[PDB]
Amino acid sequence: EAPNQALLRILKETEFKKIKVLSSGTVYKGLWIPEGEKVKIPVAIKESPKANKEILDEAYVMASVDNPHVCRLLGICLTSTVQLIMQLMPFGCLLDYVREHKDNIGSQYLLNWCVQIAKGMNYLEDRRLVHRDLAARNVLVKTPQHVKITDFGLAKLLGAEEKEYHAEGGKVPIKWMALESILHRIYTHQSDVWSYGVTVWELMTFGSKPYDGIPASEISSILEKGERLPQPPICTIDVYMIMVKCWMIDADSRPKFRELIIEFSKMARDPQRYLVIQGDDEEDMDDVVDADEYLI
Amino acid sequence: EAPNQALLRILKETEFKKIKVLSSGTVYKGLWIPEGEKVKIPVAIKESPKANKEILDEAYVMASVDNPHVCRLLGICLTSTVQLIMQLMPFGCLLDYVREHKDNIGSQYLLNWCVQIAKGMNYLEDRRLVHRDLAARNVLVKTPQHVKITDFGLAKLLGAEEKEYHAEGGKVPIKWMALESILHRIYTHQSDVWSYGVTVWELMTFGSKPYDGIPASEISSILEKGERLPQPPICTIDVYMIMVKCWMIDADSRPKFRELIIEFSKMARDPQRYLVIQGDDEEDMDDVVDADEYLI
């Protein structure tokens, strides 16, 4: 049980300019010009008071994690409307990218993505943190060969000698959820593995919707009768076998993020043995530095 | 809206002897020998007529509060110069103690202090009283493990169905003050929470001066641009996150004294997970009784 000495940097709204609306709470593309530092950092700005407790728990989790495959918070801004300042991921979330480039994505990208998401999830294991909302919609694309886990709205830090997180009520994404989570609201790192399983499936199917046209009220019944999502077209049995293991009912039986890194990594060395696919800014951009190069 | 049946005990100056000057109005160390009661109570004696209205409003507030973490008035003395008789806090105020023992104070003390000040502030919520001058200089140390809130010069009792106290003019300690208080002279229990935030910061920094070398005229501007006090060295992010919430702009968004007790309490159970610190009378003293044991 070690002390968490992450820094939370508070920013002035004078130091950053919004530019466009990425979404609509309400994310903006922007540029952050710190202190007096001859650098301009491209940022995404997330702009009650239930919403405030929520958004500062998120800030807390996000500040205390540091990994190349995990979303980077640059700071907050304590304006009336609280603001999260994050690294800009120009290519948006992975669900969309995969849908918008369905026709042009190869084995090599797909597998490396499975690797990079496992690396991020393993780091979250190490930090004893449990994401609880892993899905392709919650992976961001920095560049097409570099993705990051994001959206820690539901993330929970595991306590001392505590291995489960019993949830209360609350709206939850059922179709990504493990069975123990859905019946008993228990959440573990293994639980997160189940969702990994479905995230991989979103990717292999180029962005299909798990259990399309089915009731979330049904899902639990299905899972228990022993149904799972079907084998995508693109998938060697080697790959599908890995998803299926993520959906084992005995959570301890599933693979650890550690092993998933190793497995997808071996595969990414000979991508086409494992997936069978047909076809295999602006302004004064001079002091621009990406968040990854802006440390402190 | 219930009747306030506090007692105000009037004392003869014949019943108490001054001994030394604690400060220079003009506080004295002294001993109070009541009635005919075989007890000697160590007291601090605070010795126009603007000053008199002021000092009897203080007496009023102080008489009507009763908590282990709130300064205890023993009575007044209606001599030409009006006198407040209080419990003696031998170790003086907390700002000084923390400065004078900078090098020797641990996580455990610091956190328990944050707890005891929250307990006192919550009691003041219950009694519908608003302190308006909370700061480390206005906490007294009875023993190093037992502190009390003091100085009710500015305290105001909230009325019937009244939730704010609009102030008039008057000199005010800006650097401890909430933003709504400073722009609009509004004061709430939440407002007091902001000051708690800074009181905690005084303690974590071992007695630094908030916003050193800055103009009180600036402060308001800063707070609004979204700057706050920086994260002290000693502080887990867990602790700092709590201060920052106390300085939220939407007062309703800040934590209640209730929650602050709970939070600091959890932390005081494993002090070093949360703070990272290097090094973690006289005469016939026979009928001496401390004020806390002198009831009526």
Image (cartoon, coloured by chain):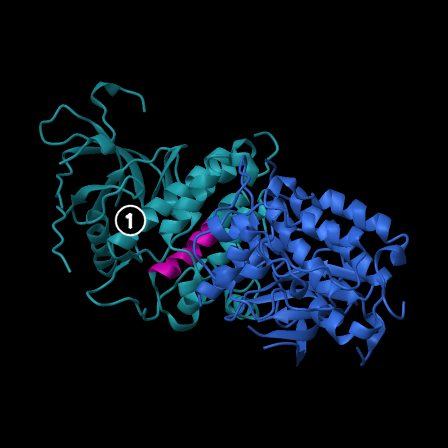
Chain colours: A blue, B cyan
**Percent from the top left, x then y, of residue A139?**
69, 62
- Residue holding disc 1: B123
Look at 51% across and 63% down and name the residue there: A216
Residue A73 visible here: yes
**Percent from the top left, x then y, of residue B224?**
53, 70
**Percent from the top left, x then y, of residue B55?**
24, 53
**In terms of image quadrants, where is residue B229?**
bottom right
Q: Is residue A271 above or below residue A209?
A: above
Residue furthest front in the image: A225
Look at 75% across and 43% down and name the residue there: A259
Look at 57% across and 58% down and name the residue there: A58
Please tell me how crowded label 1 is: few (under 14), some (14-19), or many (20+) other residues with Cα within 10 Å: many
Drawn side of residue B60 relative to residue B231, left or right:
left
**In terms of image quadrants, where is residue B36?**
top left
**Residue closer to the observer: A76 or B3:** A76
Q: Mark 1, chain letter?
A: B
Number of numbered discs visible in the structure rendering? 1
User: The N terminus of chain B is located in which quarter?
Assistant: bottom left
Drawn side of residue B50 relative to residue A27, left or right:
left
Could you tell me what secondary structure mostly forms the magenta stretch? helix
**Residue closer to the observer: A122 or A41:** A122
**Residue closer to the observer: A37 or A242:** A242
Look at 63% across and 57% down and name the residue there: A134
Q: Secondary structure at mark 1?
A: helix
Q: Is residue A60 above or below residue A280?
A: above
User: The C terminus of chain B is located in which quarter?
Assistant: top left
| In the image, residue B196 lies in the stretch drawn in magenta | yes
The residue segment tinted magenta is B189-199
**Percent from the top left, x then y, of residue B266?**
45, 40
Residue A149 visible here: no
What is the three-letter code of the residue carrying label 1? Tyr
